Image (cartoon, rainbow over all chains, first blue to last red; front, side):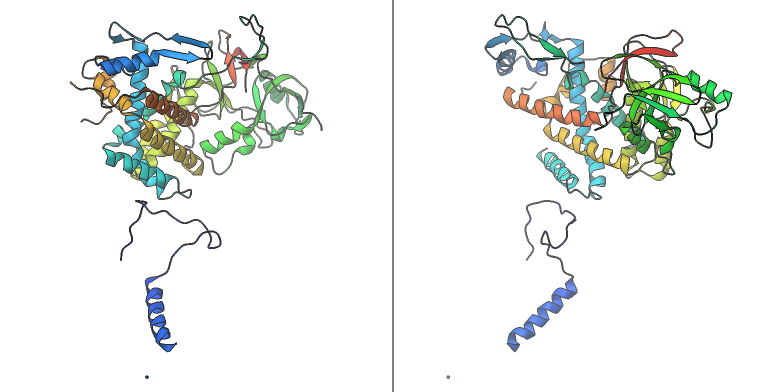
Length: 45
Length: 140
Length: 295
């Protein structure tokens, strides 16, 4: 589950979303997306 | 001069001899060894000691301030400096003492300025076939 | 376009008493900085007073003075002042305004004033709450000491307790140079010192990374067979911990030292101050000297 990383230390972010991509999302949002997709997928001899 | 203590071994002697012989355009010559009678003169000894002291002091002093300052960093460079120091370390105090060590670092840094930098005095624009002489503008 | 003027005339629009003019006459051949060059200027732009600000920091004032252009004062008339812009390499007579003692052959730097003695010297042209504040001309060792003290205070301020920071600032701010005592006013720590601290940290990191094992081990090896006051006072600063060199490679050593010189220059530059004058003469009362201008 845990990812391996090349850089030993993390760095702060000083750029807007229109120039570099960053994966950021709260845990609650992740759980909500998971359950919503779970119901959606099923919703779709 | 830095190899002065290790002169016993043949490899060090070979390195010293290679260092002595220098070649510039169409000219080859050898520079004298600053070690005489198996000993180093006091001025070159002071220079080498100053270089080594600056290195040693910086090595231990740097990390403490780097880790404090890099958290604030807005240029993502100081974190890289911290990581470089961590790699270097993995390959291997009273405030008065800290003040003394910082002041000593800077005073040993000042001792090297004669070796560290040098200034141009002439820039040449003419040369005779007699090349022993040339015309040049003076800079000071 | 309009070529830069070498002679600048300054006129006070405030009315001058005979005492004010008498004070002005004493200042001939001193160095006064100005922000911009015109044939005829007003006295407000003259001197360092315009930059005195609520920020009060010594570092920012040092930064501001570095960017002003320096002029020498030619002879005075009624309500007029004539200033001359020196040229590199020529010979000039300059006035020792400050209390610092000069010596033959040393190099002079321009620096914001720092208070000394009773702190009652400030009679210089107070008129309409404008004041004639002039920078100090000091020899290189004192400027190096001042910059070194400022940077050391900045570096030490990090993560140290507030009270011991106060104690360190108290002990560091005072300087004894050439048998005189000076003290740095308003040693504020702010962004201007922060950028210098960042560059110093970067340069020290690179110096520690670059230095070869031979360089690191020289001091340790020397102590095994030498003994001197210099060495014993030298090794007290270090952390307490036959053989042959593990790796000999003169080409690598040469390249490594070549890079290390650049890094040492980077570290040196932030305490170095540009030499403006080099002196070879002195009035035996130390009030004036003849110098070569450079920069």
